[PDB]
Amino acid sequence: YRTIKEVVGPLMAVEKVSGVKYEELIEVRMQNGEIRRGQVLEVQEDKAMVQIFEGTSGINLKNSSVRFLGHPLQLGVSEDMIGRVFDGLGRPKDNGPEILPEKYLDINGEVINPIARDYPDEFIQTGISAIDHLNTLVRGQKLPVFSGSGLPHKELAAQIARQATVLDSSDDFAVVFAAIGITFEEAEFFMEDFRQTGAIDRSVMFMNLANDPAIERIATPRMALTAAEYLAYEKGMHVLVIMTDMTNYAEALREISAARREVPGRRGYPGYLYTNLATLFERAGRIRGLKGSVTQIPILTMPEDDKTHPIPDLTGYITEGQIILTRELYKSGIQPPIDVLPSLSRLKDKGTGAGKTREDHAATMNQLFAAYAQGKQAKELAVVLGESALSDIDKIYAKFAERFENEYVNQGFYTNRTITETLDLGWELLAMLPRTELRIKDDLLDK
Amino acid sequence: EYRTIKEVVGPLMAVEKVSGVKYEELIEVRMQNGEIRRGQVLEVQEDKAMVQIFEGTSGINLKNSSVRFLGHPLQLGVSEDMIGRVFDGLGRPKDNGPEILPEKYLDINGEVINPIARDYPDEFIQTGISAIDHLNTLVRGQKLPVFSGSGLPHKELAAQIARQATVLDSSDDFAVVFAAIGITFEEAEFFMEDFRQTGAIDRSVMFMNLANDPAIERIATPRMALTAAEYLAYEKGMHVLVIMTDMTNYAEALREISAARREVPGRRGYPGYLYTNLATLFERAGRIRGLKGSVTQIPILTMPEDDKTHPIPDLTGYITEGQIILTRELYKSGIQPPIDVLPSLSRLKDKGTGAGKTREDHAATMNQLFAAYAQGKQAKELAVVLGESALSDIDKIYAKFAERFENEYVNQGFYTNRTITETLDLGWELLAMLPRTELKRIKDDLLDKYL
Amino acid sequence: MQIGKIIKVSGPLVMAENMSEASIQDMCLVGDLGVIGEIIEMRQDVASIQVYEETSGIGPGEPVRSTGEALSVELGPGIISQMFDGIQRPLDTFMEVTQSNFLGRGVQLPALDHEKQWWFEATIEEGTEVSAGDIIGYVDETKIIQHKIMVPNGIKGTVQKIESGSFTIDDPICVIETEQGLKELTMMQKWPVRRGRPIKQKLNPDVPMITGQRVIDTFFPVTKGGAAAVPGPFGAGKTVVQHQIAKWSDVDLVVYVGCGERGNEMTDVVNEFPELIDPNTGESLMERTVLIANTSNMPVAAREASIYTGITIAEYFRDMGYDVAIMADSTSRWAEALREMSGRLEEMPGDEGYPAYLGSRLAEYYERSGRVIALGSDQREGSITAISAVSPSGGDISEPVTQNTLRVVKVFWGLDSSLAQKRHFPSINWIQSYSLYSTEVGRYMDQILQQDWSDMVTEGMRILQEEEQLNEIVRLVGIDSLSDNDRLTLEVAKSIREDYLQQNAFDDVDTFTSREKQFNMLKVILTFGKEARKALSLGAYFNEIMEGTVAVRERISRSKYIPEEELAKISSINEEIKETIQLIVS
């Protein structure tokens, strides 16, 4: 098809074409001989309008050809994927072996039948005391991490990837890691940390940079998730998906939407945002009759720290809870800076207690919450005037919350705590108070 | 009848090859199955006519359907037998009796009253409520609305004013036009209960429009009732009173249709013409020179999130000749009805006070009860701000007065009627608690007459 | 029908020519793959279809077939004990046929079973003058509910041939000669979801429904045909409240709709619900339940259709004269589908991104439920009682969906996770929550219980509201700052809080409480009220009244455990008060 009619920015209009389909891959043979790949964004009787991945610069319309590849964006799935690093479209950026794929899969996949899902069963020990204890992660869950620009979410991400394990199964998670539109220093942090710890042996990495095409960014989460579902539901592996940063996906999504001349809904994002996000996020869980599973830790930055911003808002409704990272804590030097007040895991009740973790799990978590509650209420009322507004009991709460934030949550991004250790240190932090301020009847269980 | 439907886009439909179709004209749609649907001509241009169908365009086949062009805009079949009857938003036999054979058909938009032909609101309507009769006097012809909120008892008050409303001369030619706008079936049924229990039905036409009725029917509802109202007021010559519930429910429908037509949303999401559109409804109230009998309007609106600077209450405020406020704070205390008289006002009140209409003393009693109740509230204010000892003896009595003013005066229950005489009698009684020296707003000769 | 032709595929928007016979809202099988779609606009023969499935790999030239109807449901034998999505796809069946755990693109499967044999039992004799809503026979469908076969809307004539026998829902079971000719009636009928089923008359829902749950039946009751809305803050035992209603309530059937919930959260409804035991039969609660399931993952049309399909089913059982309960959770996710739907249609947005006709959609929904007179000669009375959960993002009141629901519905049970942190179950906030049916329930309750029940309930409400009055004062100063007269009242309400309001869903006896038992428990604490107030007024002091009555107040704590058989056990509390009060006269 030598019938390039128009070029308007990235977009290109091919006429008198034959039997093309929406979201089909193309190649553009330029008159110099250079080849650029592209995707169909729209098709009509005569015409079909496309967007060029690389960009449109330096193309003579007359003497350039368009080849229609016949298929959408595909991932060549293989078990030689473990230990490899790919780009946002699945080409290798590591210079290893060939990677001859067992087969090619569409990157959208198919919705899990709502009655084919299985309850998220088993406890995942992330090694992080604010998660494993207060906001417990369960295999098959979707537990995201809300953060902000210039916060250590980067670090947390790599930690959960290196530390997370299920208790006594000798099963290791395969870690599918996807980076969407992150800087170099950001991508290098990750790939280095995985090589420095042997974490890459357990991982398949999809690495998309901020200066990569906007259409590649959008592909990356779907690319990574297709490899996850593959390893999990065709190879029967327990898979843990970590993806950052979703804001960058949504941002890239706006770029194409505005390119397809689509009128945005709430807050300038597409109407179909919710579906798009659900489409990605609900590619997870256990499946009745299948060995493998997909757990999902999505990571996003909250633009201007606004909770009601569509990106953290819509993600709220879809995922079972969320993990919050405040500037207030990171500036106080908290590692990791998890604010447990707004933080929640909606499934924590499925895998905690006798024979799962330990007996005291619930009580401590609930007792630590309301003690830390008044703890930060005493601190904000301490600036009313002190100490003429702090009583004998109030003093112990600002003294509780300070040590709670410093000694309990603030553990450092390379410290790996067990559930044994987390509850013990929680007991000993609780021990700061008299047995009157309630915690079960046998509270003398640990002292 | 034209068989040429070219387009349907959402609730909007484009019919080509038409002739002499007029703007605002009424249509009907014969569907391929047999179903009939009413509609409006929004915009007519060339041989094309673009229309919006009331019940929506859901499940229409374009090829095998047809349109009839009625040649006349919205119309209400009027007759004097309409009294005691219940019609819908489009004014059809909703109460199951003998079908009405209308004298004529009036366009619901009616017509503007010539400013010179207009007679100024004069005389008095006995509402039955002390806080409206005495301090914010409703005057035949006036526009006087109710400012409310969600879960407040405006519905109770609407049902009460409809019953206790009557004139102080020939009560024989007094009627009430009641409009239900976008209310729930059980809200409707409540009004049907209170109407056919005290027999206010026997002097009233009812227009019952529902929350799930097509939005355009909700828009039409008040214009039908007002067409029915002017007809009974000039044509038949009666002092007619109009009650219309949840004006907010009206505006909700207005912005819903406005958005369907892809209209540019004005302030707070409502159309730029919100002011004017409401005026084509409220200004219909008033009197006419030489013509006996008048139209008076009592619209009801719930203030969204109690906000008075909200478009609904504000733009109504900018039109009407005063306002009647219902506050949370007073319904909280069990005062029925919860009327705060401080933020309320009737502008044309002085045309229904003095001898003949009510009583000569009316003026001073109203202006003394206000000036007192105001200071009694200012006392109630510093009462629990600097301790109840900071307000002296002079202050203390006034605070006891405001206390009895709400419980006994403003509170009167939704089922006990009060005549102006009773209102004035009880008014002087509460006033008694003050020394004759502090009662300075009243001159000497008005005083010596009332025990 | 005519085969149409794709002329443009832009994102989820499809253009097609030849669509001249199709109507607006007609459902389509777009493209070769044949994905689900709905006609939104027509220009000439060119239709504009919204496709609610991955449109990738769909190009022009491909065909577009119309189903020939708007979104409908198949109604008949094989519908109870079934799990569907918002567009009524058999989720069980889907697995067996696709042999897959995944909902594949454009795979189409009949809603009910067209190959299952049933015993159709005729109950109307030949030569009968019939109309819509008349019973022509019955099928004993489950171990509980009997499927009454009804005359479809539109048919009116005379029965020529009727036999009892074993037929599929595709076999003719009847021959009725109408004014047109022979029209065979089958076992199943269809119905557009968005259009409400016809009725003879709508009547006020005045018959209160026994939910067994104390705080509801007593203080915030819903009538059979009334509607209630519930906030859904996390950890407030919402599912527990839902399930109790779903079983204890004296409705014949239950319709549950999951609008568009979190995957794993949706699986909890799927697992838990069938394992609910029907209070009366002992059989699975499914045997009288139709359940709708929708992950957020589901096609947006399905998420939007969710409550409409649900209530269309709920109505088809109401026409049989049964009492039906429809539960949807949440209606916020539904509204969230409407919002997206609005966005994709390029409409002028209303408030906070919702379409301007949101309040209208809700009114359209909540007014389809009520006490009715069904069609047919029998003039049978059915009802739909509506229970809807709302999850307002950050748990909020301001949000439009909540405000518009609360503008049309009568009852509001406000779940509070602070009262759940205080271990108060069920977690309903007695101050915030309300029921408009209260003063109406007084009429029916005083009538049927021969007592002053309304005088009792509204008194308890003066006490509980006065508690919050005093709790503001107690927390203000200290405790002794109140004379014995206040100090008494604070405990009276505490007795209501722990002995009447607090109810355990799991305890074999406390799980459900009937009218008498409820009336009694309410009275025997109210009998304590007036008696001790006369005791304190004539000299006797606070401390004297309390320390000694412990023999009966720790036996008042037991009231909620007395079996229904042992009526007079609580009735005898009215005696022990009059004696122990006479002990303080010495």
Image (tube, coloured by chain):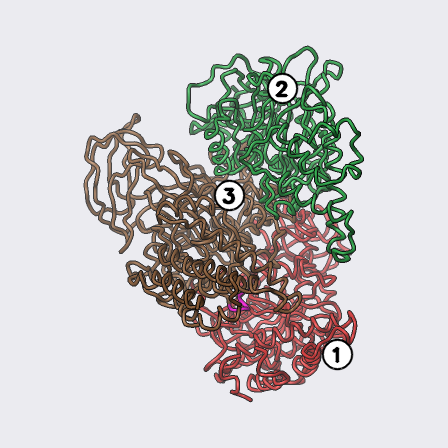
Chain colours: A red, B green, C brown
Q: Tell me which amino acid carries mark 1.
A: Gly
Horizontal side of C215 relative to A207 (left or right) equals: left
- Where residue A424 appears, x then y in whole percent? 58, 86
Residue depicted at x 26% and y 43%? C171
Instruction: Tell me which corner region of the image, top left, top right, bottom left or bottom right, holds residue B325.
Output: top right
Chain letter of the residue carrying label 3: C
Pointer 2 and pointer 1 on the same chain: no
**Is C422 included in the stretch rendered in magenta?**
yes
Q: Nearer the viewer, residue A18 or A189?
A: A189
Task: Tell me the residue that label 3 is attached to.
Answer: C38
- Where residue A409 appears, x then y in whole percent? 66, 79
Task: Tell me the residue that label 1 is attached to.
Answer: A333
Q: Decide: marks 1, 3 in contact (CB < 8 A)?
A: no
- Look at the numbered disc 1 and give the secondary structure of its residue: loop
- Where residue A178 appears, x then y in whole percent? 63, 70
Q: Tell me which amino acid carries mark 3.
A: Glu
Pointer 1 and pointer 3 on the same chain: no
Mark nearer the viewer, 2 or 3: 2
Q: Is residue B9 visible?
A: yes
**Is C2 included in the stretch rendered in magenta?**
no
- Look at the numbered disc 3 and give the secondary structure of its residue: strand
Chain letter of the residue carrying label 2: B
Pointer 2 and pointer 3 on the same chain: no
Q: Which residues are magenta?
A: C418-423
